[PDB]
Amino acid sequence: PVYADPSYQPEPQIGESQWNEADANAAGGRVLKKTTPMKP
Amino acid sequence: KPKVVLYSEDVNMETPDTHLSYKPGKGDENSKAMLGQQSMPNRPNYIA
Image 1 (spheres, rainbow over the protein chains, first blue to last red):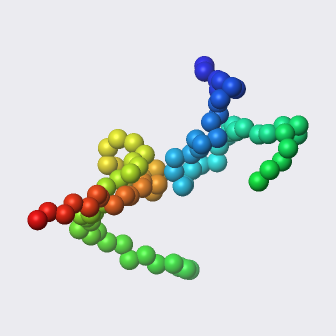
Image 2: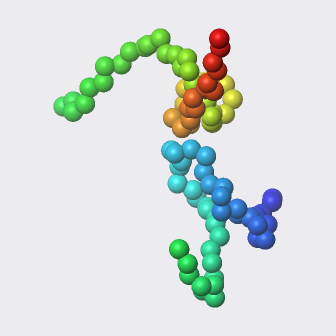
Image 3: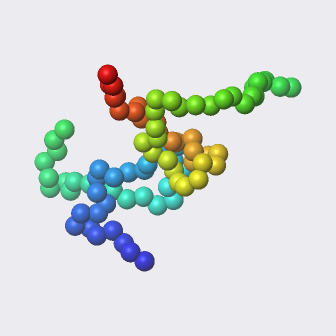
């Protein structure tokens, strides 16, 4: 029962390994808080 | 009524100048996962 270490996981450069992936029942990812200026 | 027809056949499958850059798992058994295998060209090698 290991969870993602929030300080660096999930790592933005890691995703699914194949083009034909089955929709995930549960997914994760990082996101920038509203307090960080938006840039392209 | 049939809308699509597929002429299925076996062929002498080869991959003489490429190798897999990604294989779902172990064993070369056909599966849905195998649809995502990735091929990569072999390294050039001039000999003379």
